[PDB]
Image (cartoon, rainbow, N blue to C red; front, side, top):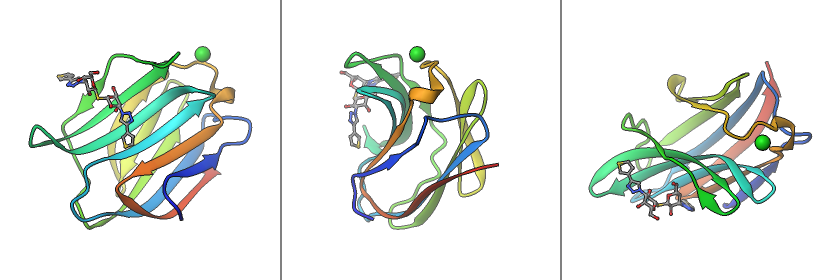
Length: 137
Ligand SMILES: OC[C@H]1O[C@@H](S[C@@H]2O[C@H](CO)[C@H](O)[C@H](n3cc(-c4ccsc4)nn3)[C@H]2O)[C@H](O)[C@@H](n2cc(-c3ccsc3)nn2)[C@H]1O
Ligand SMILES: [Cl-]
């Protein structure tokens, strides 16, 4: 698939919706981003950073009216440059639940409350993208 990639989420997200992204991190990657969007707002920005002051960190945030909110940071970093990955995002009633390569990574409490209006997923950054899909579990 071409990156950046836009995956429509028809009628928004709902609990029990599982989104699966398969790809490979490019060699010498710098960043990856998944952006769950409600129009121009970003309900959930998931942003692995491969070199922030020589550390690897995952940053999560929400953008409302073009302004970023309080960052939530995770030091557990399951991505490796050059290697294939699977990201699964499970929508639960109170949070997005993220697993990478079948291991739980983090939860992100819903800041944007109108789940039915979060109708696009943007995928960008330093990856080769193989597949992006969703199903109900
Ligand atoms: O909050 C998320 C946003 O962060 C900003 S960078 C942000 O800048 C601030 C000053 O304006 C602070 O410096 C902030 N900070 C917070 C901390 C901190 C927090 C706790 S200890 C240290 N140390 N830096 C730092 O993260 C990125 O630019 C945004 N971004 C990424 C992308 C993208 C596109 C394609 S792939 C990625 N498109 N927009 C997005 O990730
Ligand atoms: Cl809302």
